[PDB]
Amino acid sequence: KEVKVYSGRHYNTDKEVYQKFQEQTGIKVRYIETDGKAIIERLKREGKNSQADLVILVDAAIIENASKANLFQKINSNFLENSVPNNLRDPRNKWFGLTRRLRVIISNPDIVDITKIKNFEDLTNPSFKGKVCLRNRKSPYNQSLVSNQIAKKGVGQTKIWLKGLISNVSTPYFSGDSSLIRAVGLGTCGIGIVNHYYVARMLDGVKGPRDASLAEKIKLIIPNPAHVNITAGGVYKYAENKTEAIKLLEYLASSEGSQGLANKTYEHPLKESSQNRIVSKFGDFTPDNVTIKELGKFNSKAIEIMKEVGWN
Ligand SMILES: [Fe+3]
């Protein structure tokens, strides 16, 4: 009995969780970890000849792509249907949330007045002209942030928000969240938008002393209410080991599994906030109730309006 996992959780952290499942169940886990988009393209090409049983992907945008590519099958599990929060799973039961991450505001309080910053709407303030830095629009994290704004506000108001935000950027777009964190730490940027867990990995010395020194200079601001995004798992449409994939998905979404995945990456488990002291110091959050399905729905439109306003 074995299960083949193709995981887009490309942090090189999750091996120990699969090993704990293996010991407890006797089912051998064969895992590949690489880029989620490489996994989607590989499965489309392999189709019925693929060896994937369980697919793990990061970000609503990538889950939506996989869903559109018909990569998942609907599964029956009393545990997942009754234990995973409804907003963090497919209403059609093809994928289920495993961890939570927040896309937040980071600021250098020597460069900008952080008492003027509570939510994403504040970043349009003309006192931040030339102080806002962003990762580029190719990041699913940024697409899903804009889709979140569309979900709630509609296209018109999101476009007005975007024009205001992009008006305040005078720096080329970053190609990563960690390089953005460094720029805000250095003070070349006043304000950024990044995933909370990258700041926690730098503060913990995972990326070495210079990155930890820069991360200490940052103030992290959780918008209230908060935009939540996820990593999710689903069973491959042609899974050979369907039963074993479900058992593993059930373990990953369980309190033990979700805490095991989230603790490696400084993410939040599915149903409780992280017990990590560095993550807890960032503060409490309340989710805005936008569903992960809705972030998928508006992805095409987010990309179109990001291009229109010149988020590049
Ligand atoms: Fe990430």
Image: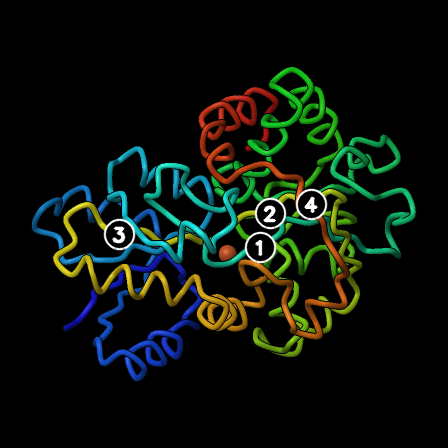
Question: What's the residue at 67%, 27% (across, down)?
Answer: 162
Instruction: Report the Cα–Cα distance between label 4 and label 1.
Output: 10 Å
Name the residue beneath numbered marker 2: 228
- Confirm if mark 2 falls within 8 A of ligand 1: no
Label 4 to label 2, Cα distance in Å?
6 Å
Mark 3 vs mark 4, foreground winner is 3
Q: Position of residue 68 (x, y in %)?
A: 30, 33
Structural distance between the alpha carbons of marks 2 and 3: 23 Å
Check disc 2 and give the amino acid type.
Answer: Val
Q: Quadrant of residue 8?
A: bottom left
Task: Report if the CB atoms under discs 1 and 2 are less than 8 Å apart.
Answer: yes
Residue 235's disc is: 3
Q: Amino acid at mark 4?
A: Ala
Element class at badge 3: strand
Q: Which residue is mark 1?
A: 101
Q: Amino acid at mark 1?
A: Arg
Q: Badges 4 and 2: C-beta atoms under 8 Å apart?
A: yes
Residue type pointed to by label 3: Val
Q: Is mark 1 within 8 Å of ligand 1?
A: yes
Residue beneath label 4, please? 226
Element type where label 1 sits in the image: strand
